[PDB]
Amino acid sequence: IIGGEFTTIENQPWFAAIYRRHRGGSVTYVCGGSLISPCWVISATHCFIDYPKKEDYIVYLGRSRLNSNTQGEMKFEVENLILHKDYSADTLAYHNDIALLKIRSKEGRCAQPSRTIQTIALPSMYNDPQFGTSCEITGFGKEQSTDYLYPEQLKMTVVKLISHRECQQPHYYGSEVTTKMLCAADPQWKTDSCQGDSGGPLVCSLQGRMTLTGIVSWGRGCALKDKPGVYTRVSHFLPWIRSHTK
Ligand SMILES: N=C(N)NC(=O)c1nc(-c2ccco2)c(N2CCCCCC2)nc1N
Image 1: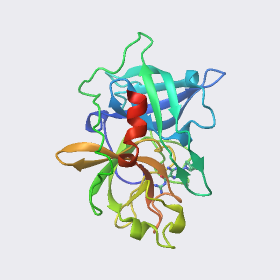
Image 2 (image 1 turned 120 degrees about the horizontal axis):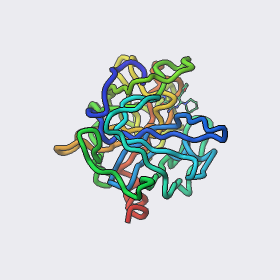
Image 3 (image 1 turned 90 degrees about the vertical axis):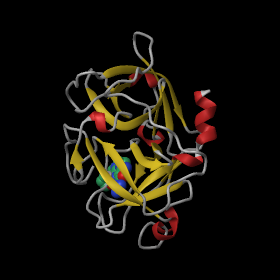
Image 4 (image 1 turned 180 degrees about the vertical axis):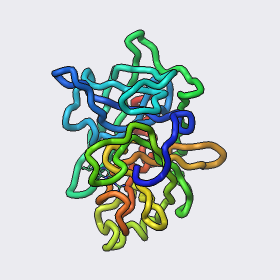
């Protein structure tokens, strides 16, 4: 997250931190995710497509720090890693950048809600907030594009939804953004998602509760002028999601 603020998991209790185990036994951070029901975390396919073996992934819930324990955190293995059959990666964009991780503890259980762990509501199909609406993004991703390290503490910021009309201008993303994506940016281009925030939540109030409107997918640079964050439009994927969560 570029700009924004440090936060704790209690302000974004649906946030999931996804890591990969490596042959030496080194474990490194992969991507964010969001808990949409006790047994299911939603994220982005591009995070996993290069190594799609479920047995190498670890999901944390209730976690406020990247490389140390938070009280009340829960660790899960991945019982099913479901990557979108039509995923593809273009030159800039990813398409159908959406993945589901069925989580199960080594003790055989799904997530139990707490002060630090809650599910996030899904939107109604094809229901999105109006453009100009302020939404929240969260993650352990880079604080600058050029950074080598990820921050140790979870971050959050606020961005505003941009119209497709605006996002599709040639000096924004032109042809590369589609209707299955959503753009969001800071009006002054000061704050943004970045590398390492992929798969994490874009949350907006829709009706009267916080709702998962987007999944961090891609952008050119981070917090660069005329280059918004691009997000998977969750409201376009409910049948896909329901097909696996049923
Ligand atoms: N909102 C944005 N402006 N940007 C991002 O969301 C974003 N940005 C980057 C990135 C980092 C540096 C330049 O671009 C990035 N990367 C970089 C390596 C290849 C792609 C996947 C991971 N992933 C993202 N999701």
